[PDB]
Length: 476
RNA sequence: AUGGGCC
RNA sequence: GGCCC
Ligand SMILES: [Mg+2]
Image 1 (cartoon, chains in turn yellow, green, brown):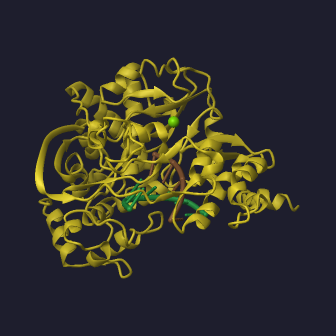
Image 2 (image 1 turned 180 degrees about the vertical axis):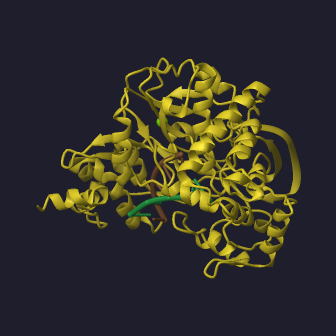
């Protein structure tokens, strides 16, 4: 978005930290072009003359303003997508109880009991367990008073800027392109879950191309479902965004919230209001307070869902701005936040859509290599989604999610102290789809030091997971 | 080190 | 706890 004000205050919010990711035995074997993101300004790995603080907020370039006619078009697209979504999900969207918002429901998992509480709780000590009883599903006086202000629509907050401690390609580590997490206050998260929690639960349960959302999916199982769907289409596109989250303009955000979360769809009047508080935000980074207009914070409840919904409306908006007679059945798509797979039997010109996405402030580029524009004829076996390719298994005849071996090497090369064993088992479930030979090669540095699951055991587990009859058919 | 998923 | 977004 657009940075409107940068104020220096006395209170310093500690963010820097040291990386908790330590190199494993695999690091010296694979030597990946990957490493922990730069968390300190004095990190020796950083390029000369790179100020980490400036690069972080460089994503905030502008808040794109839309014309009345483009806003009118966007409203129509939001309402059209909002028609499809609530037709599939239903309109049972009344507030969740406090208990349900904390403990979760069918389709919505519970709030994490010991994550960051946000501001101003971080400046007072106080963890999440002191403010909220997670076992009993009850809130203390501090949150109670905050919830009363949100009901009154008088609630004010600040986002706490956190540096994301993660493995990144070495090019981005050296460029100081450390990702950030905007940690919202725990009460804001709770109330959002109250306002839109059942909707979110319904979204998760009904994931698929019909609603254009993969949020809630299990790639082990659903790659067959998504794979067979997109294989039916003549053209498949792999579309990359540049800073998707930060580039959501105030106009697009406000209109989407207005059209999707209407009281006539069963929502409480405050559902629209609580989401609109995400448009103009105050961010706290050390001694600096930065006011931003536009863009989506990442620590919000249902940030993935909001981004997914916007992604759906963006594609409809861009296509209607270029072509005539474009409807929801003109194409098909699945998204997860900024990640997107689009397909159509019509020879759509995504290169011509570039300016139309720009009117929203979004920059689309081909993922199909960083090549000379968008091309036609590509299939689902050519694309990546959720860092996974669509490969066929020749033992079952099903699509399986295959990650790049270079990426799996990177994941196995770094781990938090004392978590290596459980990480290996977790990564084994990802690595099984690379085939027996590659699975063997990936875990070979760990042999004799940790338990590695046999390829066979994870394969048979997966066969049953994707299709229970297929596992039984091998016994018939 | 986080929202939201999934093991 | 890990992974993806
Ligand atoms: Mg992509």
